Amino acid sequence: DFEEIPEEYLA
Amino acid sequence: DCGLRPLFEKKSLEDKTERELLESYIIVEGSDAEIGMSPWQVMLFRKSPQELLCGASLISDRWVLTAAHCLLYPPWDKNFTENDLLVRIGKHSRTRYERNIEKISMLEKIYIHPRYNWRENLDRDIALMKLKKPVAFSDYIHPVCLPDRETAASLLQAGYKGRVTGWGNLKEGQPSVLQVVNLPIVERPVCKDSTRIRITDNMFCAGYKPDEGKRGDACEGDSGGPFVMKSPFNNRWYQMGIVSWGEGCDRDGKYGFYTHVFRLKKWIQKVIDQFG
Ligand SMILES: O=C1Cn2c(Cl)cnc(c2=O)N[C@@H](Cc2ccccc2)CNCCCNCCc2ccccc2CN1
Image 1 (cartoon, protein in one colour):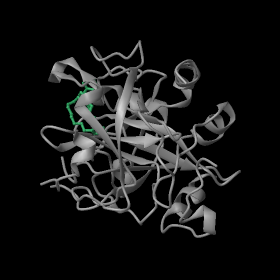
Image 2 (cartoon, chains in turn purple, red):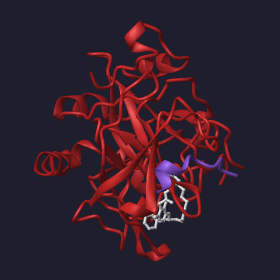
Image 3 (spheres, each protein chain N blue to C red):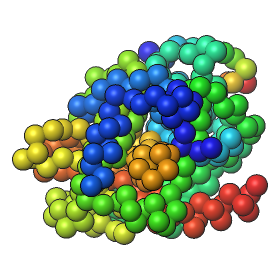
Image 4 (cartoon, each protein chain N blue to C red):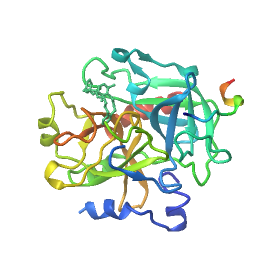
């Protein structure tokens, strides 16, 4: 149930 | 400037329970942390699937301290590398993305103590993680201090209380926000006699005795988080331990075990100055 974090950190 | 919290020491405000720690210098059963109460708290976050990995702590603008078993533990097929994780600093809520408050950093390199004993008893359960870029300090992001010999000798005494924080399980479900609990350091003989696991000088245990009434302990998910104490001498917070291991959570007659930070400071310093 973790809110999605912005894409910049996952790229 | 380590160990001085922007929202407390910096503005001469005390949190709800630090007095308990001072009076002793003579997460299960914890409570919600106050905002900015543990600015050095770090959340180790797994990228895929997105989940809580471990706790950790901020010791400088580019270094994060945690438990070696959070990154490496063969018995449970755990062997994470830099790109498998992210570090979230300045958080309060466990699951939500705290826009404009928390900062997410990518890992440049992980360094696990060379003599970390994952085969037997987690002896020397410590690891360092260097961030790719420095994180900006703020009201919610601030480094904790590491103890020198004097501080360790004076505060690491049976009866003296420390503070453990984490987003781990509330029972042996999950907390909405960061949890905190103050626990007393336990005499070596008692720690030894409470388990069949071999205890080493690189560990210390904490928690209340059955006849003391009060409760509290770290639990799954809290690993790698800090066990801190507020020095009564210079009023700065020092990380004396790292949540390491236990048998169950908050069980009567059992105690949580922590990595003795000062004992391994030699290694910590060696890593930092050698690798920037
Ligand atoms: O899980 C861990 C680390 N950890 C690991 Cl990697 C392996 N085995 C653990 C343990 O505690 N506990 C077992 C006893 C044991 C201790 C040390 C090495 C091998 C076995 C006995 N069985 C597993 C218990 C797992 N939950 C432990 C929850 C808990 C409680 C207090 C402080 C930290 C922690 C979390 N830390």
